[PDB]
Image: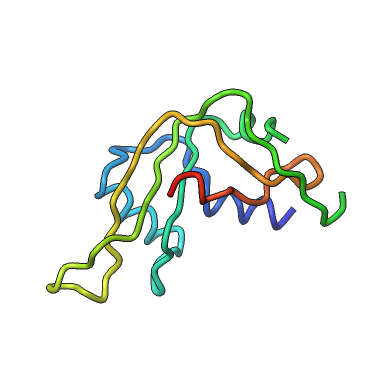
Length: 116
């Protein structure tokens, strides 16, 4: 499903290096979440099977996972004058239960609000 694979593109990174500001700068860029800059974005780590397991037709049910996941949240921050155009991110990494919308047994959206 395209909603699900879009979810993976925006919110899944199996094995992250660093999980710091530098990590956020890199991954937001390569997942196409810059130009224009996305305001906040959280990545869930670990294996893909465990995320799918949190969850017809275009109806979505909101679910919080029963176990926690390693996550890294990238939040848009105050740009430096030397590259005001570029997207500057602050990373917040943690072990959190995640809230997703499930459609047909697959996660298709992440509730970004709880990581704000």
